[PDB]
Length: 141
Length: 141
Length: 146
Length: 146
Ligand code: HEM
Ligand code: HEM
Ligand code: HEM
Ligand code: HEM
Image (cartoon, rainbow over all chains, first blue to last red; front, side, top):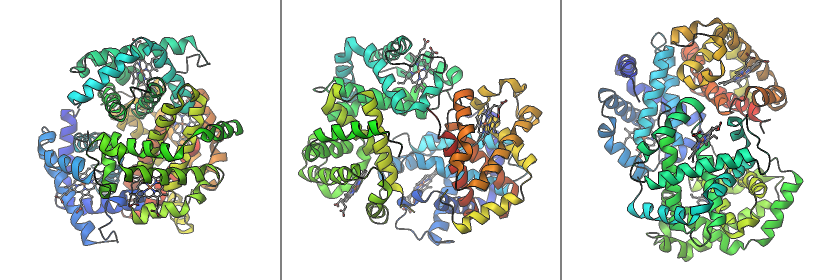
């Protein structure tokens, strides 16, 4: 349950991310691949090499999803209907990986928005990513 | 989301447990503690010794809940509201633990309901506890 | 990993009673029915549309025995699981790209079938001990992932 | 852990630059803040009502340098986190009754704090390294639970 303050925090947070969201997405994927090499069994057709266009590209894709989820902080289930259709019925990504993508997202955020990455921001952002992973894995069964 | 069929199976199997839910409830618990001893950390004030009266008392309450949740198959979140509040605000029981106990509850019926424990039901049943677990963990945040 | 001798023996004892031909089948079969997303890896197997489609599938049936046999062999080297599963672990990663979690689903499914077939004979502590085994096999199978 | 010679120095050298006091206090501070339920154990600390109220609590900061210390000490026995943490392992279980799960949370939170602190320096591969340690440490503390 996102609190108005969380929503506010998120908006704030990501507001900052601004034009580097794609770069971050990119960074966070690369970061997941390295730290949790099992997350890779889902991208056998990618070039997981440092600075790959596939990862860059994909980095972009996710960043954007994230973005849309923020402006729609209030109606995620609806805004991410298609992504959850895809992940539940096509991709079929095991839920625990979301926990890993999310961690990774926050590692990168913190490394990049020091002044903004406060305890309460951190908290909101944990909750939100958590919120979106919940959306993404709800049509699982 | 339980299908009509899911529902039907749950009703049928729980139906057969009927009368022994308490002892199955309790056995599930012993199964739990014995197989996953970290779960024990939440009952530090309990006599966990074999044939513990604390444990059997405890198992009864848990099958009771299930029976009531079975009975409110169409309104679980509300019927279980009471209990959801407890585990989320008092007990503060890690969600992980839940998948451990559904596990053993699943294991116990299997050993008690041989003719009923078909793939279809095993399947419906897994979905159900998965569902009950979901409600119980809803108010964590 | 941490199998006391009495756990080690209780394990072995029961395992004496198992019909790997048929237990394999029910484990895999049931796997495919309980967690239908696991179907994705055997699209090759044909009809999996129904529980009977699956349970009965001769293909499902045979793979199950292959699986279970690999497993049985693993029971005979409870001291060097990692090593025992070394080549299969790489295969699972490098070739089938099977997320390792899949291995703990099979582990749990399995415990159910033992429960199912052994009933009362499958006591808490025996459950307890089997639990360590599949825990250990899944870890074993995931060791070479990268 | 299964730390690469190479990975062992990255870990080793970053840490070298750690302001134990500072890092210490913020990780535990952020623990309680990001995961409220973790405060069910530090009732005794006082006002944990608010972020600033938590981050401010000196009993909190104090406890933090104490934990980081142990961590710090464990980084020097990366070949034996198990034996290094056994006594502490029995404590959290037998005395504290902390579910091994919270160990994992802290791990992450320390990663986030380090990420926070070193910016650029906190490279993917170097994150890749620490991740493996928070991993081992968490696991070693969990070790003696029963
Ligand atoms: C924070 C949660 C996540 C978000 C917001 C997210 C978002 C997205 C987006 C926007 C796409 C693009 C789909 C398209 O090509 O139209 C996508 C696809 C994909 N996602 Fe996710 N994702 C998340 C988590 C994950 C995780 C944890 C994994 C696996 C570990 C994953 C695996 C994939 C894969 C394999 C694809 C397709 C890539 C390709 O084949 O090009 N996703 N996701
Ligand atoms: C199938 C999932 C579960 C169900 C249906 C369930 C049900 C219940 C019920 C009905 C109560 C008693 C409330 C009362 O006093 O009126 C209870 C209490 C409790 N539950 Fe759960 N529970 C579940 C999972 C868990 C898990 C996984 C844990 C921890 C590993 C847990 C820990 C506790 C504890 C510690 C208590 C309080 C016992 C006492 O001090 O008397 N529960 N639960
Ligand atoms: C501990 C559990 C498991 C063991 C011991 C095991 C063992 C095996 C063995 C011995 C083979 C044959 C190797 C070969 O073809 O050279 C195999 C193949 C395979 N395994 Fe596993 N397996 C396990 C779990 C799984 C799971 C859970 C999945 C999917 C969710 C899976 C997916 C596959 C697939 C798709 C194949 C190849 C099928 C084919 O022949 O086309 N395995 N496994
Ligand atoms: C691997 C990570 C951790 C390490 C190395 C660690 C280490 C320590 C140490 C050295 C103490 C000293 C207390 C004494 O000697 O009496 C302690 C106490 C304590 N720890 Fe941990 N800890 C860790 C994680 C956690 C987590 C994640 C929690 C809870 C969420 C926790 C809860 C506690 C509590 C409640 C105490 C009691 C302090 C006191 O005596 O006032 N610990 N820990």
